[PDB]
Every structure is written in C-alpha cells, then in structure tokens.
Length: 390
Length: 167
Image 1: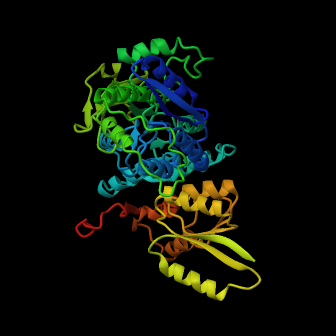
Image 2: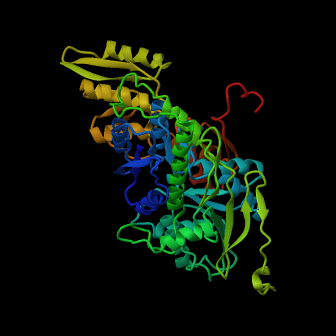
Image 3: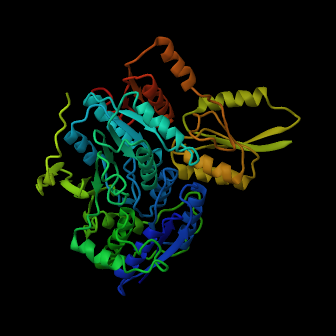
C-alpha cells in the first residue's frame, strides 16, 4: 500500500533526514509502502511553509512529517487543525493543546525545575534563546514567584554572528555585577558551544561556577572543552547510548556512508535525528494498526487547493489522529505514550552530569515520580581536596 | 481612481470599523476612490487569515488594511514581505524589523521604563497578558538586569473565563 506522506525537512537538517532514511530502511514493509514527498525548504518562511504544505495537500498525503519553527507554530496548528491532517514533528512542545500535532520532543520544565529543586538554587542567571519559544522562560518565572527566586533572564538570540564576541564579554561582566556563579543556558547546540567558548575565553569554567544545559542533547555538545576546567556542568539526555537497542543503531550509524547519509558517519547522534528515526517507528506501527483496523483511509489525491472557501476536512485523517495517540512503542527515547493532544507521556529523561571522568548519570526523571536519583555511586573516586580559606 | 484595498477586520472590532467608515467619510475624495474589500474574519485562525489574504491577492488590491494577532505576526510578516504588498496595521509593534509593515501603535517600553525610572521602583510585581506578545516582558527584564530589579512576572492570559475569580 503506497501511502503518500510528508517530507518538510528544513535545509541543513540532513542528519535527521539521514536517520529518517534509516527508518525508511528499518521500518519499511511490504504491507504498506511509505511514499515520502520530500520538500527541503526553510522552516522560517511561513509562506514557503504554506507552499510545501498545500502542495502536499494537492498531493493528497495522509500524514505530514517535518519540523516547525516558532515562525510556523502559528502556521501548522492553524493549518493542520483546520484541514484535519495529522502532523508528526520532532520539534519543540507547543504552547497550547492543538489537535493533529504529534510531537517527539517531550516537556522539559518538569525535569528542569526538579533539577533546580535538587540544586536548591535561589538566585541564578538564565540566558535564553528565544528561537525555541519562551514557554520554559514562562515556566521558570512561575516558579520564581513561588520559590522567591531572583532569576536574571537575558535574551541572547538577537545578537548578530559578527559581534557575538564582545557583547558576551560585556554580558558576563554584567553577570559579574551580580557576581553570578550559577548560569543555566537555553540555546541551540551551536549557540551553546559558541557561548561556552566565550566562557573559555574569560575562564568562568573554573571551580566555583555551575552550569546547566537545558536541552535533551547534553551528550550532543562538546564536553571535552570544559571537562577539566573546574565548573560543574549538568544537563538532560533522552537518548542514552548505553542501551543495546541504541547500541545496535550506533553500530550501524557509524558504519553508514557519510556521502549517502550525510551526518551519519559519526560515533553519536543528535536527539533530533534520533526522534526522527523514532517517528518512523511510530508511523509504521500506525499504518500497521490502520491495516489492523482495516479502515480504508485512501482519500483521493484531488484534495486540490488548500484555499478552498470553505475548505472541507477529510474524516479519515481524524481517525489517524485517534490511532496515533494510541500508538505505544518503545524507541530510542524510551517508553512512548501519548495524551489526547499528542504530548509525549511516560517518558524518562536521564539526567547526565559532566564529571572529571566524563558525563555521568545521577538520576533519571519520571513524569509522576519526578526525580529518582540513581545510586550508581563510585563516590566520585575522591573528595576533591576541600578548600580551607583563612 | 478606484483603488482596491483591504478590509481584514477582526469580528467584534466594529468600533474600529465605525471610525474606519468615518475615515471613509472624512478622507474619501474624487481624485481617487477607496475600494474596501471588507472581510470580517477572526484574526486568531492563521488559516482564515491566509484565506482572506490570498482572496485579496486574487482581488489584486494595492494595499491591505487590518489587524494582526500574535497568531498572525508570523503570518503577515512572511506573506506581505514576500508578495511585496504593503500592509497597514493598528496592532502591536513587531519583534523584528519587517518590510511592508506599517504600524499605528508605537513603542511603549520607552515611555514605560522612563515612568518606572520616574517612580524609582526597584521591586514591583508585573502581571502580563501574553496575547500582545512578550517584547515588553523582555523589555522590563533587560532593565531588571541593569537596574538590579526584583520584578515578579506572572502570566494571566491562560486563565479561563470561568475561574478568573478564585485564581
């Protein structure tokens, strides 16, 4: 069964598209054929988003896969919710409960605030990139009212690439107006590494400082640059490489051709690429269940223009959303369960902390049992020579 | 000269449309005729925004007038900036410098922060609705880093109409 599906990959995200093709290798079947309509367009231009959206609406696809920007979170929720096409995304969680939104990145603030409750911080700086939204920024300020916090939030995303060198030296000096030692970063993996290299330039990676990286890719960043400086670096990892099911992927992942699968011939993988591979496992089990439902969803490809007034929905795509939210599969990100809105539940975030030996787990995050500390204890191998001032 | 123009008024904003018609009374002329294409649609649904937008693009209007939501600030800047149609809005200021955006509400943070500098406040609560954006919320936190402020910001826009009494 050839099933036309979406391919709205942002340009420059080909490692995700590489592991998407591994999902096309691993999870294709003769029971039904996945037919991607690959459109490598920029996710920022909502006009260009709308063009590849309505072309696949003119194609008559039964599901659409791709990322979404904050420039397109107002697009995809308004377009897929009206035309009743289920959309599968590995991007950031939405602000509101929108229908036809199946997300692969779970919530982070529950693991994030429990970590700050673990560290028991009261005054700490919080740099943030506005590009992934501001809901986590809204999340920390709601706890700042309750926990009497004195968090200093400063946006960093509007700083140009030419002068992200001198503004940052101005920035941490302004953090030394408060003499902060506790900075939780909220940036992209490149923008994380750029600012840490500026911390390297000024030397605030020394002992006395503490940093927390607020993403699921704590192992994705470069930890060797600041492993031996003195500051203690914490973070979250949803894709734990110690699993053999992950290790079976990695043993294939490094042996993948870089020229055929760009970004694949590596030792590790981004979590965004892993969730892209995890999403194909969900989509395969979906149409295996839609075959198990024996429900003919084969709407014709003549859905036509999305600018039909009124634009009629197609009711089989509503049932696709009903079965997608009932898909419960194990993947690289662990146990996957959904709500009635497409949000991931029963997931488990592994809190990883960089130590002298490397990144090491102190505990996993649970949705109902928030922080359960792992007693994997080598006692840090020492006592780190307690500083006695006089 | 009959000049086709836009009419994307949000529903329930008819006092604005009333004074729009007074502008049609006061500022119409025989030198050129304003031809409104009035589309009273909800500004939240960006799909419905796109329908009345491209219908006026199919109309061939020379300018488009109407409001924009924060659900459509990512729409109108992406659509009017690409199709190169000038857009006139009385809505809130944009976050970025976008072309073809003519705004009627000016900036507020320069008057706002100077007022707090007048009152010389250091710790003060700041309730905010997220529906007009968060740039002013970003504005006060940038001054909070400089002026050592202890501002408590709490969102209020997500509270339902049924229980906006006990919360």
